Figure 1 (spheres, helix red, strand yellow):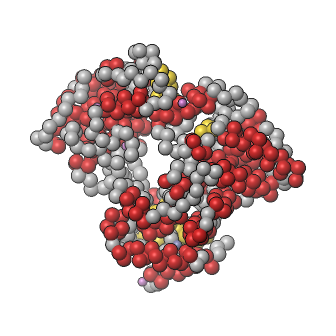
Figure 2 (figure 1 turned 120 degrees about the vertical axis):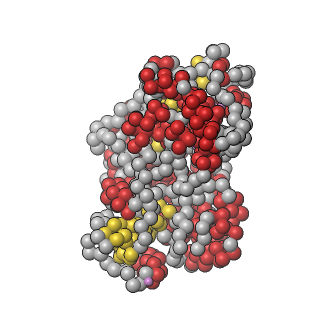
Figure 3 (figure 1 turned 90 degrees about the vertical axis):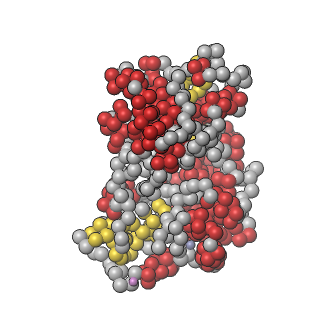
Length: 586
Ligand SMILES: [Co+2]
Ligand SMILES: [Co+2]
Ligand SMILES: [Co+2]
Ligand SMILES: [Co+2]
Ligand SMILES: [Zn+2]
């Protein structure tokens, strides 16, 4: 049921821009989204992402690995947009029960107060926004008008439009903040600025760093997460649990959005009203355009919904972390028996929850590592595994397990999945112990073989390959195939070309210098600061184990690849052209 007093102004402006073709399509497919109308549009998107020809030429054995090549096959055409919508986005999560709602409000109020003890909400500025625009992903949709975000921020007319929308937000109205599905949702840059202005502080001021949030890992980096998992495992308690949620963003409820909004209770002045506009007008009452193929050509559908979360927003990461922290705390409460029924919370139970949060709240937060929808929890004991009523009633249904089957955890932290990795102790030649990340190698190579844009020059393609190679040399040096592949890419691309997207692999610094900085000098879990003097000193995983986040070391095709790698390197060099290359292949 749509509230036209909040969304009608947005819908009418779109309707007036397409009055001739605007119509209600009685054959529309939307079930749990409110459908408003359609108009004729030009099809956007493509049914395949571009392959990185440099990386591909240097990773020939993986041409026949289906896991690798399947990753290249995206579909952003109207046909492709409707599949993902039908499968993932067109669902409904039931409203939580009264007791669940009271648990969430109490916990969320407590959590915001903890996060705000040492932080103060503030407004982010146009200059902050303009500086970040001169970098990358703001996730704006630029359509018929500017050509890029860098061109828009320089134009004075652009900020006049922002001012017009901002003034409307100040009077509690919204007219241009519309989501576009081209599942990832885009907005026009002015709508992104208004959200960044109101909520960017959560990221800019590191509200979910581990120091400030205890559970969060914002800013940590892959080379630190394994150490953080190992520290959590040192706590007394039950097994470590890491349940994935099925389609987290689609399971964010209106109740969740309202609890995330209580961060406005910590705000003042026009900042509070601006953030309240973002929450009520654009998060809890969203208008979405999505393309749909019809026998008569592509149409754009205008649809709306209150409850879900739009992937790619400014506060998406932080608010997902907030709500997951809140959800996992409540599951810890349920396991410890702090309340007994989610149908309603007795006044005695409500005081018990409040006392539990005051007594042990911060300790229980430190038993968790949470990044967006990704969580690891080491609870007090294993009652957690079957404490499922609040989690299911909040809509956070676990993936790949029956609704009421108890969760299975791990007693060995090196088996716990987190941020799509597992983490291992790696013994150096001098006896020091690294905790390194491991991920399936086919997935790593498949992602490096994907070019991010369309119509990229060979130089930008080569610099993206170099960026992957250097990330591999810093994060996955312990995998035989990736160290070799990284060396080949860096030998094939001119040494002075800059890798193209903050992260430590994004310069032309000597990668051994960066390795020493990351893993030794600035590594707080590395007491002996003696640096290593060569790559030969830096070890691999066991040859049995290395093979098995995906390696091919035992294969005939890999042995041939490794032996003739210089031929492929020379081939790439002949295309970039006469240039100055460094040989990294020892
Ligand atoms: Co018209
Ligand atoms: Co990269
Ligand atoms: Co190198
Ligand atoms: Co430490
Ligand atoms: Zn707006």
